[PDB]
Amino acid sequence: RDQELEARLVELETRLSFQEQALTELSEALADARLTGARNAELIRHLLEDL
Amino acid sequence: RDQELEARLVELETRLSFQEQALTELSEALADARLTGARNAELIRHLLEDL
Amino acid sequence: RDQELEARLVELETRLSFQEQALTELSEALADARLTGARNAELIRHLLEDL
Image (cartoon, rainbow over the protein chains, first blue to last red):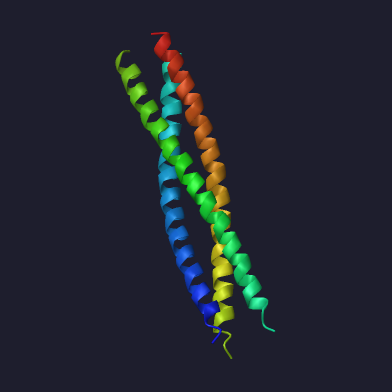
């Protein structure tokens, strides 16, 4: 009758699944942001020079 | 006497809670960073043009 | 014979460990990205002024 433990496992599994998905999305978005940062930095270095 | 399992559940629950909180904070900070990137890109596109 | 529960715990522990590691790496990378954003913004503010 100790199925309290299994219900909790099911809850943690579910939470963990959402976390995993969130993480993947945050990694993708950050990879893109970092590339934009890198590009911007390089554009700026140039503008600085042409002045 | 197999309460070893429940202690472990409690540990994972706790770990998961900190992860969730961390994720939320990282999402907020990234959303802000991305907007700054977007703004910067647009400012730069202009400077490039006015030169 | 209900060792099904322990195997699941072991799986969640393992998943959680990878998540934790991923999070740490994403936090580091974001901290760096944000600093680059901050720098870029300030470089740009200046260029805007010198024009």
